[PDB]
Amino acid sequence: IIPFTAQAYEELSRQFDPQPLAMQFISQYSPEDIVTAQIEGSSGALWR
Amino acid sequence: ISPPSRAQMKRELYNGTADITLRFTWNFQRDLAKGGTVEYANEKHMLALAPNSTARRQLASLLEGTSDQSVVIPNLFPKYIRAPNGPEANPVKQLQPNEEADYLGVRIQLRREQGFLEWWVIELQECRTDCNLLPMVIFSD
């Protein structure tokens, strides 16, 4: 999990800047707020 | 551990210069009937695994194929923990002065007895019956 930095936050906000409310969400949430969901995908755990 | 990442874990202990996060989370879930807001008192006692250290070289051979390596984890099993009704398994300082070097010498033994049948016994540096029953203490509040 990566706590998004100020620069990272700017990136996300700019990605969704065209849509006002999209950018709003990101921008309103404080920097080091938006966290990165780097969920693991590898298995190993077989299933039962 | 997923096979590609198991081989990567291997590699780390084998060579890969990285520090495996050995978070020894000591979660202490109590109850709420007798009170205890965040009953679960937890603390990840992490041991950054120095790349190919004595412990990690034992782990290299552990994950190579042999199952007879007593991985020396420098005193990292809190034998006295002042846990309260909050979410923290903080050990008592002075009870364990170093409290990272005065916890309790813990050992690890992966028992891959192909028949890999990878088991994992948590031993002690001085395991008497603490390979199956490690006796620490939680100073409860």
Image (cartoon, rainbow, N blue to C red):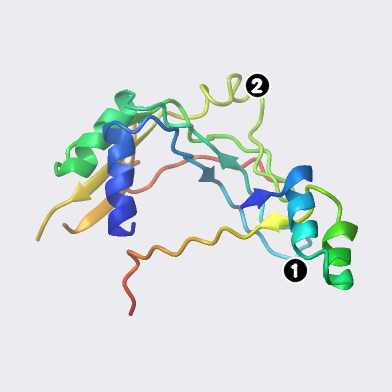
Which residue occupies the foreground of this view, B104 or B139?
B104
Q: Are marks 2 and 1 in contact (CB under 8 Å)?
A: no
Which residue occupies the foreground of this view, B27 or A37?
A37
Label 1 crowding class (10 Å Cα cut-off): few <14, some 14-19, many 20+? few
Residue at 76% across / 44% down in the picture?
A: A7
- Where B74 sits versus B13, above or below? above
Residue B51, x across and y down, in percent: 37, 27
Disc 2 marks a residue whose amino acid type is Gln
Residue A46, x across and y down, in percent: 31, 71
Q: Which residue is mark 1?
A: B33
Q: Which residue is mark 2?
A: B94
Looking at the image, residue A28 sits to the left or right of residue B89; the answer is right
The secondary structure type at the circle numbered 2 is loop
Residue at 75% across / 68% down in the picture?
A: B33
Residue B73, x across and y down, in percent: 39, 30
Residue at 89% across / 65% down in the picture?
A: A24
- Which of the 4 image quarters holds residue B10? top left
Disc 1 marks a residue whose amino acid type is Ala
- Which of the 4 image quarters holds residue A47? bottom left
The secondary structure type at the circle numbered 1 is loop
Residue at 16% across / 57% down in the picture?
A: B116
Q: Residue furthest front?
A: A18
Which residue occupies the foreground of this view, B43 or B123?
B43
Residue B131, x across and y down, in percent: 31, 43
- Quarter of the N terminus of chain B within the rendering: bottom left
Looking at the image, residue B86 sits to the left or right of residue B100; the answer is right
- Where B84 sits versus B18, above or below? below
Which residue occupies the foreground of this view, B25 or A28?
A28
Does any portion of residue B49 appear in the rendered image? yes
Looking at the image, residue B102 sits to the left or right of residue B7; the answer is right
First in sequence, mark 2 or 1: give its number. Answer: 1
Residue A15: mark in rendering: none
